[PDB]
Amino acid sequence: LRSCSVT
Amino acid sequence: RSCSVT
Amino acid sequence: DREQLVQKARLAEQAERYDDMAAAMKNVTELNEPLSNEERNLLSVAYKNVVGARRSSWRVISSIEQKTEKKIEMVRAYREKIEKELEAVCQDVLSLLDNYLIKNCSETQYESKVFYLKMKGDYYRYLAEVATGEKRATVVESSEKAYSEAHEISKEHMQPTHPIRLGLALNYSVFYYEIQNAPEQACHLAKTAFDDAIAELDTLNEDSYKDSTLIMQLLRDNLTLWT
Amino acid sequence: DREQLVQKARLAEQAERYDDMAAAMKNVTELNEPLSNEERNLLSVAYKNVVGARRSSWRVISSIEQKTSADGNEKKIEMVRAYREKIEKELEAVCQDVLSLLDNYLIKNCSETQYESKVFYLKMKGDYYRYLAEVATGEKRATVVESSEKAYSEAHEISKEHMQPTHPIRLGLALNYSVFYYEIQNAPEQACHLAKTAFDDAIAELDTLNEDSYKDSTLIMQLLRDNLTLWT
Ligand SMILES: OC(C(F)(F)F)C(F)(F)F
Ligand SMILES: OC(C(F)(F)F)C(F)(F)F
Ligand SMILES: OC(C(F)(F)F)C(F)(F)F
Image (cartoon, rainbow over all chains, first blue to last red):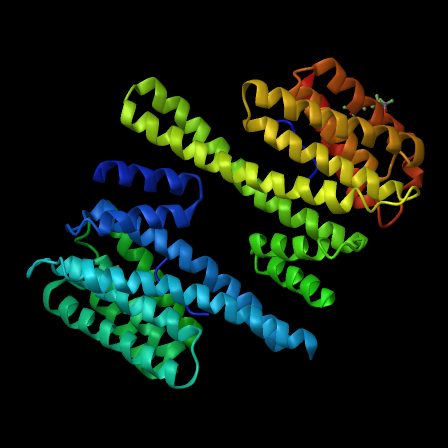
């Protein structure tokens, strides 16, 4: 996975 | 709609 | 460097940058040599995605315009902006077809001849989708003329199970149904193509069985939709 | 007319033409009038999609470049490198446009009491400097990294003082700020501390969730937990 930002 | 070549 | 332009088109496809992919394959085409089957497919995939994005946007805006006064005139102007973009894409493809691709077919490269003439019919059909009045009648005639030329070559030289012959029948029948509003002609063309390909389905290998049955499913789905 | 530029941006979004959508909202912003909550979202959605398309392409190209470099064909290596640079130039031009709009219109026209707008726009400023840092190297990277942290830090102090912990803008700022710590600054402990504090602060006031904040806030709470689960 990767780090998630505001979607 | 009708389908054409995909 | 031809091989590098092809790599750039592959790279653009993975990056989902289809305008870049089309620019690369347009550059390959302008080298004025016959395209390999690999290059032919990259060119077709590129422009299909480029024009397809405009067709999808046009259909959204056109539905909004119908389903929806100061806002209406803005919607009509935005639709025309999209139309001008779509028409410029088709102009580039049709110029590639008439100046390089159809021209560079040898006398007996009938597969490529049908492929490119069908493509010519396709892109005039996309022009007709967004045209009205006398301008529409002109590109409708051009689309029919290209499909008809492809059809005569395909009947003479290709077997009914050939995916390009089947795909020509599919798109030509869509032209009849959606553009000419001639559902009887559309139904006859699609049914004849489906039935004539049924004969030699047992003869196909695993790969050809998949490609041909895929288009036969689309023909069948259209026929049930139309009836 | 302004109402026609905004309706054109709404049209462009429905047609998934985000370049057009950003151009329309850029024009609305340059009218030097404040943006409504909806117009603010239209502007954010447009540029997020425009810059997001380049970020997505950049990641794929960068992954292909690594495999290509190992195989050692110098012509192919140089082709992929030049294509990455082309996308990097496009991404940097998008970021500069947004940042110019933020510094010259959006942040500037915020009154002393428009805390929510100030946090939103300063968070946006930290975001687009973070996107620049993602593709920058060397001294150009340290500069945009320092500008990203300055904008996030100011946004955080305003948000802590004036906004509820479950507000989606406060939660979203904490999420993106913690991503900045982890991915850009490589400071996992700082990243985890900020995300965990914002998460618990909001959970403690879950009963304050309204029908207009529930979906947005709980989505960001889930993402904070997902990042925390990944980083630990
Ligand atoms: O296998 C034939 C096919 F393809 F189904 F038409 C048969 F007609 F024999 F069933
Ligand atoms: O919300 C708390 C936290 F911060 F997630 F640990 C608790 F675990 F207590 F729920
Ligand atoms: O769900 C976690 C818990 F359990 F609340 F600590 C997290 F901290 F990640 F939110």
